[PDB]
DNA sequence: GCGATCAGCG
DNA sequence: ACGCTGATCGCA
C-alpha cells in the first residue's frame, strides 16, 4: 500500500542531508545482534535497503558517519550500538522519537514507533509486535512485509518530528531533548559498547566457595527445623515457621504468610532458624543473581559484560540497567561487596575511578524548598544522614556505624516523601506515638520542607502534573482521585518526583559536561557506568591524578543551586577498591 | 506471567 | 501507611 523503492544498490538521492532512518534490530538485547533491514525516507522518496548491501557500501557508511547529514530516528542508541558492533559509526542524529515521546509523557510506556505515533493520532504504521509476533512465534517476516513496515516506521518518524518538537517547545522541553537526552544517548551508547571487563576466574572461585557455605547453612536450617523442605518455598517456609514452629504471624501477603526480611528480623528473638534463613537467602542471592547470572552474560572472548541503560523507562528520569543490571551490584554487606573485586579495568595498567554526589536529593530539596535550616546545613557541609543517626540511636558521631547511617537515610527520605507514623514505627521498632512526635520534631526544624510538600501537592492538583528543574514532566491524574488510597500514592509521587527527577537531570548534565572535558583534555579516561548519583570510569593510571581534580569539578559545576554540590571520589585496581 | 523477595540508588 | 528500579524463583 505505501510506495517505496526496494533498492538493490545505494544511490545519491538516498544520501540527502536530512532523512528519517530506520536500522532495524529486532532482538531485545541489541548487543552483537543482527541488523535485519534499513529504511530511509527523505525529500526524494522512500527507500528500503538490505543491510548486507547498504552496510558494505562505502558512500552509505560515510553518510551514516557524517554528522552534517541529519537523521530522524526512533531508539537511535539501539541502532548506534548495533552498528558499532558492525564496526560502523552513526553520527548526526538530530531527533529521536523515543526520547521525545518519553519526555512528553513517560507513562505512555512508548516502546515502538506505533505507540508514539498514536499520541498524535497517526496510525499508518503497525506495532512491532503485530509484525514480528511474540515468544516462540517471533520471527522476521517475508522481505516485502519487512520492507513496508520499516518504510512505514520511517514515514511516521518523518511526519511526527514537527508536531513532537512543537509540543516539547510548549512544555519547555525542547532543549531538554536536544541538549540533554540526545547527547546523553550517544554517550550511553559508548558506555554500553565499551563494556566492563570481568575476572571470571575470580567470580568462578567465589561461586564454588559459596556453594559450599550454602549446603552448610542449608543443613543447619533442616536440623533447626527438625526436617527438610524447600527453603525457597513460601508455602513450606510459612508452614515450618508459623505452624510447625508456631512462631508469631506479624504480616500476611495476598497469598499467605509473609517471610520478608523485616518480619524474619522481628522473629529473631523467638527461634534461631530465622537468622539462618536470612543468611541462606543472602548467600543464594549472591550465587543466583551475581555469580551465575553475571557469568551467563559475560562475552567469553573479551570477558566483558555489556549492559543496556534504558533511557526511556523510569517515570522520574532516572536510567535503569538491564542484563546484567550493573546498578545493583552488592555493596553493603562485606560478603556481597567482594563481587566488586571481579570488575576490573579493560587494559593493563588502567584503574577504576568512581565519583559520586554526596546527599544529592536533600541538596536538591533544600534548593527547591528554600528551607533556611536545610540550606544552612549544606552550606556547612553537614552530613544530615549521620546527624540523623546520632539523634535516632542517641550516639556520638564516632559511634555511628554504616548500618545506622543507611537506616537514618531511609528515615530522612521517608519523612520528606510522606512516611506515616505507622511505617516509621515499624521501620525503627519504636512506638507509633514516638514515631509521630519524631516526625513533628523534624518538621519543626525544616518548616520550609513541610510547605514544599503541601505546595507541590496543591500544584499537581491545579496543573495535572509536576516538573523537575530541567522541565522533565510527570502527569499525576490520580491526584484528584476520590479513592483515599489512590490519591495518597499520587500525592507521595508529587512530593518525590521533582526531587528525584531533578537529581537525575543533574547527573545527566554532569555526564555530558564530563565527556566534553575529557575530550578537550585529550584524555583516554572514559565512562563505564552510571549508578543514579555515581559515575564510574576507567583510565590509564597515568591519568588518575588529573581525574581527581577534573571529575569532581565537572560534577560539582554541572548546575548552580542555592547550596553547593559535593562529590566524593576514589580509584583503585578493581571496582571494589574504588572506595 | 505474577507476586514476593531482595540487590542497589535516593 | 517514603520513592525509583531489575533478577530470580515458586506458584498459596
Ligand atoms: Ca552518593
Image (cartoon, coloured by chain):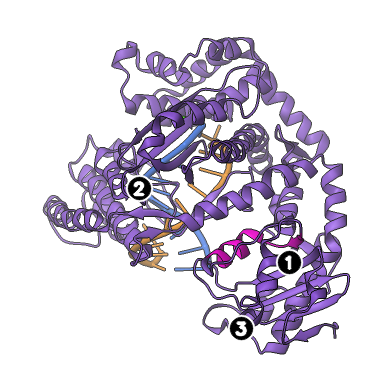
Chain colours: A purple, B blue, C orange
Q: Foreground residue, A448 or A427? A: A448
In the picture of the structure, the residue carrying the numbered disc 1 is A113
Report which quarter residue A296 is drawn in: bottom left
Q: Foreground residue, A22 or A277? A: A22
Q: Position of residue A212 (x, y in %)?
A: 14, 56
Q: Position of residue A404 (x, y in %)?
A: 35, 24
Q: Of label 3 and label 2, which has the lower sequence position?
A: 3
Q: Is residue A75 magenta?
A: yes
Whether residue A121 is visible here, answered yes or no, is: yes
In the rendered structure, the answer to whether residue A352 lies left or right of residue A420 reads left
Q: Foreground residue, A238 or A505? A: A505
Q: Which residues are magenta?
A: A69-84
Disc assigned to residue A345: 2
Q: Is residue A377 magenta?
A: no
Disc assigned to residue A292: none
- Give the residue displayed 68% in from the left and 50% down from the top: A182
Q: Of label 1 and label 2, which has the lower sequence position?
A: 1
In the picture of the structure, the residue carrying the numbered disc 3 is A140
Q: Position of residue A274 (x, y in %)?
A: 23, 44
Amino acid at each position: 500500500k505505501m510506495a517505496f523503492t526496494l533498492a538493490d544498490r545505494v544511490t545519491e538521492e538516498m544520501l540527502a542531508d536530512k532523512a528519517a532512518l530506520v536500522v532495524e534490530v529486532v532482538e531485545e538485547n541489541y548487543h552483537d545482534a543482527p541488523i535485519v533491514g534499513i529504511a530511509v525516507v527523505n525529500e526524494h522518496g522512500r527507500f528500503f535497503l538490505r543491510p548486507e548491501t547498504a552496510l558494505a557500501d562505502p558512500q552509505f557508511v560515510a553518510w551514516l558517519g557524517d554528522e552534517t547529514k541529519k537523521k530522524s530516528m526512533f531508539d537511535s542508541k539501539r541502532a548506534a550500538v548495533a552498528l558499532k558492533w558492525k564496526g560502523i559509526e552513526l553520527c548526526g542524529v538530530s531527533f529521536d522519537l523515543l526520547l521525545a515521546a518519553y519526555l512528553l509523557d513517560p507513562a505512555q510506556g512508548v516502546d515502538d514507533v506505533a505507540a508514539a505515533a498514536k499520541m498524535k493520532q497517526y496510525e499508518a504504521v503497525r506495532p512491532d509486535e503485530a509484525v514480528y509476533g511474540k515468544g516462540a512465534k517471533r520471527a522476521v517476516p517475508d522481505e516485502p512485509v519487512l520492507a513496508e513496515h520499516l518504510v512505514r516506521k520511517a514515514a511516521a518518524i518523518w511526519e511526527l518530528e514537527r508536531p513532537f518538537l512543537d509540543e516539547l517547545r510548549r512544555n519547555e522541553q525542547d532543549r531538554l531533548l536536544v541538549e540533554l537526552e540526545q547527547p546523553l544517548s550517544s554517550i550511553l551508547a559508548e558506555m554500553e559498547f565499551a563494556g566492563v571487563k570481568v575476572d571470571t576466574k575470580r567470580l568462578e572461585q567465589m561461586g564454588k566457595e559459596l556453594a559450599e557455605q550454602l549446603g552448610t547453612v542449608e543443613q543447619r536450617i533442616y536440623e533447626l527445623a527438625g526436617q527438610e523442605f524447600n527453603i525457597n518455598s513460601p508455602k513450606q517456609l510459612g508452614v515450618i515457621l508459623f505452624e510447625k514452629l508456631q512462631l508469631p504471624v506479624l504480616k500476611k501477603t495476598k497469598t499467605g504468610y509473609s517471610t520478608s526480611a523485616d518480619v524474619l528480623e522481628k522473629l529473631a528473638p523467638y527461634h534461631e532458624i530465622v537468622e539462618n534463613i536470612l543468611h541462606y537467602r543472602q548467600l543464594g542471592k549472591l550465587q543466583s543473581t551475581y555469580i551465575e547470572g553475571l557469568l551467563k552474560v559475560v562475552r567469553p572472548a573479551t570477558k566483558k559484560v555489556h549492559t543496556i541503560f534504558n533511557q526511556a523507562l523510569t517515570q522520574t528520569g532516572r536510567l535503569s540497567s538491564t542484563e546484567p543490571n550493573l546498578q545493583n551490584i552488592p555493596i553493603r554487606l562485606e560478603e556481597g561487596r567482594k563481587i566488586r573485586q571481579a570488575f576490573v579495568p579493560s587494559e593493563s595498567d588502567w584503574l577504576i575511578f568512581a565519583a559520586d554526589y554526596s546527599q544529592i536529593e536533600l541538596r536538591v530539596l533544600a534548593h527547591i524548598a528554600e528551607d533556611d535550616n536545610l540550606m544552612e546545613a549544606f552550606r556547612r557541609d553537614l552530613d544530615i544522614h549521620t546527624k540523623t543517626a546520632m539523634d535516632i540511636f542517641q550516639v556520638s558521631e564516632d559511634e555511628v556505624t554504616p548500618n545506622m547511617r543507611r537506616q537514618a537515610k531511609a528515615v530522612n527520605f521517608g519523612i520528606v516523601y510522606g512516611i506515616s507514623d505507622y511505617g516509621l514505627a515499624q521501620n525503627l521498632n519504636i512506638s507509633r506515638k514516638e514515631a509521630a512526635e519524631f516526625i513533628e520534631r523534624y518538621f519543626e526544624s525544616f518548616p520550609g520542607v513541610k510547605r514544599y510538600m503541601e505546595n507541590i501537592v496543591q500544584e499537581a492538583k491545579q496543573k495535572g502534573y509536576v516538573t523537575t528543574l530541567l522541565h522533565r514532566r510527570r502527569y499525576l491524574p490520580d491526584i484528584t482521585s476520590r479513592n483515599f488510597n489512590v490519591r495518597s500514592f499520587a500525592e507521595r509521587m508529587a512530593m518525590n518526583t521533582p526531587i528525584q527527577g531533578s537529581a537525575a537531570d543533574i547527573i545527566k548534565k554532569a555526564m555530558i559536561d564530563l565527556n566534553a572535558r575529557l575530550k578537550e583534555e585529550r584524555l583516554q579516561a572514559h565512562l563505564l557506568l552510571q549508578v543514579h548519583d555515581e559515575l564510574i570510569l576507567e583510565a590509564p593510571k597515568e591519568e588518575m591524578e588529573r581525574l581527581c581534580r577534573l571529575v569532581p569539578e565537572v560534577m560539582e559545576q554541572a548546575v548552580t543551586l542555592r547550596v553547593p554540590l559535593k562529590v566524593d571520589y576514589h580509584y583503585g585496581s578493581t571496582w571494589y577498591d574504588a572506595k
